[PDB]
Image (cartoon, coloured by chain):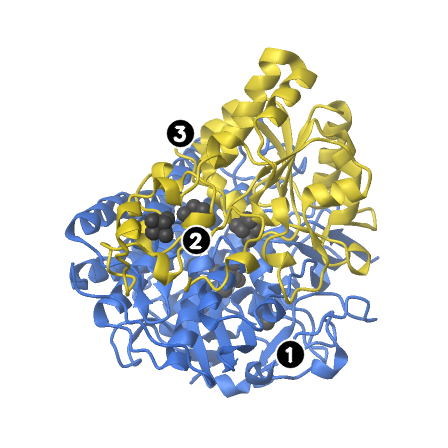
Amino acid sequence: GRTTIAIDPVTRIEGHLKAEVVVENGKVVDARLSGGMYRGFETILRGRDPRDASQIVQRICGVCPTAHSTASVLALDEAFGAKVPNNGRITRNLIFGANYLQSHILHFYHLSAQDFVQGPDTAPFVPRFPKSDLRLSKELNKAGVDQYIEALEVRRICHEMVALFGGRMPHVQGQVVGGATEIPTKEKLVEYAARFKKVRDFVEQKYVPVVYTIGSKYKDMFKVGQGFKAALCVGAFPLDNSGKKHLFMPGVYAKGKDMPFDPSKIKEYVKYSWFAEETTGLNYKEGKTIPAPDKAGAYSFVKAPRYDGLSLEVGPLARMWVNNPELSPVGKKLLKDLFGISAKKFRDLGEEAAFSLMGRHVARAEETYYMLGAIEGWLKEIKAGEDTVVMPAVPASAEGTGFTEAPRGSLLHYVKVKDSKIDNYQIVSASLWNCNPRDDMGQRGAVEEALIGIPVDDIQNPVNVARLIRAFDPXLGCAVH
Amino acid sequence: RPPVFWLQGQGCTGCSVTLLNSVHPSIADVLLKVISLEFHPTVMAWEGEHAIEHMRKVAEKFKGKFFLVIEGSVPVEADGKYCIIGEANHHEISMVDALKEFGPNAAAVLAVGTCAAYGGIPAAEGSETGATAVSKFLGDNGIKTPVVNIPGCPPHPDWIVGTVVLALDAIKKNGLEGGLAEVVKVLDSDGRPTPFFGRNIHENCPYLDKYDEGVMSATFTDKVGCRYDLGCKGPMTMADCFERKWNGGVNWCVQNAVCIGCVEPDFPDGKSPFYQA
Ligand code: SF4
Ligand code: SF4
Ligand code: SF4
Ligand code: FCO
Ligand SMILES: [Fe+2]
Ligand code: NI
Ligand SMILES: [S]
């Protein structure tokens, strides 16, 4: 009757993840996700000069380091009382925004595309499952492979963009407490815009169209992977200097309702996580990280974050649903031509289709297009030569919280300073929200729940399990830190 | 195209990402013309025990001849449970166990990045997983396979590709044993290839004249002065970033901010605080 399938390592994600599912009558009926690697950044940071955090935290993840850099310097900005100059705010946006482009392009092509596209007959594209359910024509499959290859150069170009004002990538040097370390010159801004145009052309002409196009061959993948249909966004990319307007505005979506985000409602449970029992149910401001790798019953190094008791998901789908922006022109056209769907804004996709395996890939492509617009604007707003940094003293006692959106979803860093050193540092990351285990009350994590109902018609080739997982763009380095 | 297995222990995937940024040759040419990347968790087609078994079949076929790349450190505490990298037919495989299995049979182990080479951030003050460098772990376990350190956090793609190509060339011109002996010869006392790590940043810094005059920038955005007062670790750091620079030559740490000594065995604790002398 029931078959249990364990997949370790889950590949073409970032980091170490084991998935265990139970399959009955061709459907997933239960799921467990295990984060199997722990480093302990939250304890490693204790005792350091707080300014060090904005370097140390990036090593949580070399795919999304600008995200942790940003969350960290925002926390430090608050703790240090530093007012980032206008031009420094914009520069930070150009550094960070460029990596959104790198990360979504990397994810779709280099991690995800093999879910639907057969690569060339050589490693690392073979071997794979004998029955991989690859449905594309000769022509469309070749377009996928050609674009995979081209996307390797395009993602590299995105990191040149990051490095222009960020110093290098991965692990930027250019974001610090008080702003950005390097004023953009006219010459380097020309260099950033030149590369940006190449990236824009690829996103508009290749990336967004291939996702809808492949999607139209896999329409069944819009019918599964709904999970809780609940979403979190904490805001990202400040568009002014008073902390009001952001590119992505904060909000929670659950049970058909939109509501404001209140960070005090965040709690982290650890019953099913390898941490000391006494540390369960803590808000990040009182967070504690005491590993307990032998604790009975637990199955993950990922804590279980809950928002007012709710298990939520994060990422491009969450942001685009919460913010409901207008769809890309290509997306509108292809939704009409290939899907028979009239749509103007993202929610016109409908809740069921948007919260689905394929819906998440579509959201990520739509968001990439959306970011192009924001970066275009920042390129016109930035002023060459205007200072981008202030040099604040280290406070003796302080605290700060930085909220932003990593490419994979909501991110916050909390820092407490005592005796001019880090007293506590707590990280609540994107894939923590997605790839977490059960909470103390037995409620599954977002991806765990989204796995329920996933088709496995062939237990010998159970391809849809990791297909579902990959749609969330999991990052277990981030989830565990 | 010699087979390569890429194991991730306590890594951040940044050493993989930096490799993706290789300009000449492109990562495409590396993957299709230089090496055969048979196992790599981030990018390979297959998954789970199937991926693990594939690596095992190739390792058996190329015993003594495959290259083993390690990204990240190796945690020894709690019986290796701080890093589980796979499961074969219900048997969990920790990083500790994978290194004990594949390490003896590699032609060489390439410890990529400061975590793998020296322990790095996972080994730093306040950690508790027993994060261990590759050469020390192998030595503690009686495994004599040669190890080459290519540190940096992350390394420049040129340091990784360059070391691989160096080693592959040395093996083609002297055979396996002679080739490795040739590689060992160009390593410094910390196992780093001297073509990339043989020169000091500070001695070749374009701001050395400012340092000697005692003209120090007081804010990051002042690009005229030396960055020493802002915390620059160039004086203590052995790498060629000053020349090669980063991400297609568009910038480098000293021009943009400060050097943080990322290629050094004591990184990070010995290079901290980063933002003062
Ligand atoms: S050396 Fe640095 S970039 Fe590489 S795995 Fe370690 S933390 Fe990541
Ligand atoms: S301290 Fe740094 S910026 Fe100054 S001369 Fe030395 S390497 Fe250059
Ligand atoms: S300049 Fe310093 S911190 Fe930057 S990559 Fe080179 S050695 Fe590492
Ligand atoms: N994007 C990204 Fe990394 C994750 N998950 C963070 O935060
Ligand atoms: Fe955390
Ligand atoms: Ni990440
Ligand atoms: S990022």
Q: Earlier in the sequence, mark 2 or mark 3?
A: 3
- Check if mark 1 and mark 2 are on a common chain: no
Q: Is residue B98 above or below residue A398?
A: above
Task: Tell me the shade of chain B.
Answer: yellow
The amino acid at mark 1 is: Lys
Tell me which residue sits at (61%, 20%) in the image: B182
Do marks 1 and 3 both belong to one polypeptide chain?
no
How far is mark 1 from mark 3, CA to CA? 46 Å
Q: Secondary structure at mark 1?
A: loop
Position of residue B211 relative to residue A417, above or below, is above
> Which amino acid type corresponds to the residue marked 3 in the rendered image?
His
Q: Secondary structure at mark 3?
A: loop
Quarter of the C terminus of chain B within the rendering: bottom left
Q: Is residue A41 above or below residue A466?
A: below
User: Which residue in the protein does label 2 denote?
Assistant: B233
**Chain identity for the colour blue used in the image:** A
Give the camera-side residue of A178 and A281: A178
What amino acid is labelled 2 in the image? Lys
Relative depth, front residue between A213 and A374: A374
Can you give x and y, in whole percent of width and height, for residue A112 in the image?
A: 52, 47
Which residue is under mark 1?
A288
User: Tag 2: Cα neighbours inside 10 Å, few (<14), some, or many (≥20)?
Assistant: many
Q: Chain of mark 3?
A: B
**Residue B24 — which label?**
3
State whether residue A249 appears in this view.
yes
Q: Chain of mark 2?
A: B
Q: Quadrant of residue A364?
A: bottom left
